[PDB]
Amino acid sequence: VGGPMDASVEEEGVRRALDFAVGEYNKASNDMYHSRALQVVRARKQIPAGVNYFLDVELGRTTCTKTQPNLDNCPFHDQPHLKRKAFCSFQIYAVPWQGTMTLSKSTCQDA
Amino acid sequence: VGGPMDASVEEEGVRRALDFAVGEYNKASNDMYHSRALQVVRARKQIPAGVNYFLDVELGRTTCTKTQPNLDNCPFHDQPHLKRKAFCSFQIYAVPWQGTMTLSKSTCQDA
Ligand SMILES: [Cl-]
Ligand SMILES: [Cl-]
Image 1 (tube, helix red, strand yellow):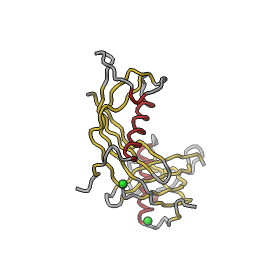
Image 2 (cartoon, protein in one colour):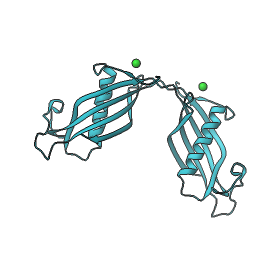
Image 3 (cartoon, helix red, strand yellow):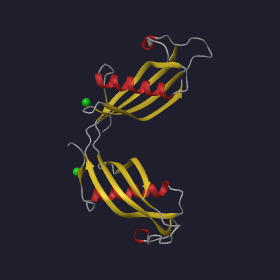
Image 4 (cartoon, helix red, strand yellow):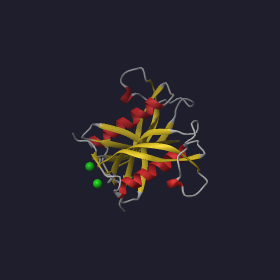
C-alpha cells in the first residue's frame, strides 16, 4: 500500500494535531461561534522522505517571450527601461522517490 | 549550527530544484518575457525530520462565542437554522524537535 497508517486519537501527537487544526479552522472562520470536533472519523500518520533546497538566485529578464524557443541562453535586456533584475529566495520541497517538487517559499526583491 | 548545508549547483537535485523554481517564477509572472538565472548566490539543502498527520473530522458549531470560556465541552446548536456540521479533512505537518505545526491542507464539506 505505502500510505499513511492508522493512529489512535489518544496518541499525544494525533491529539495535538487535532487541537491545532481545529484551532486554525476557528481562527480562519468568519463565525462568531466556536466549532469543535463532534467525531474523528479517521486519524492517520506518515513519515515523509523529503529534502529541502534553499536557493538564493539573481534573475534577469531576457529579450525572449515565453512563446519562443532556446530560452536558456537568451540574452538579457540591455535597454534602460526594459531590464529587470531580481534577487530571489526559493525554498523547494522535493520528494525524490515520488519525483515531485513544491515551491514552499518564494520572495524576490529588486536588484 | 544545525541548518542547511551548502550544495554545489552542479549536483543533479540542486539543478532540478533551480530549473523547477525558475519555471514556477515564470509561470506565475504576468510578464510576456522569459526570466532566467543570472547567478546563483547560494544553494543549500537540508533533510527535514517531520511527520504528517491526516485527520478526517466532523465539526459542529457550538452555542459558545469565541470570546467565552470552557469551549471544549460547549453544547452544539440545536436550533434548526443555527446548527452547522461539516466534515473536514486536515493534513498537518509537524516538526517535533522544533515543536511546530503547519496546516498543509484543509477542506470542509457540509454534513
Ligand atoms: Cl510515529
Ligand atoms: Cl542529500
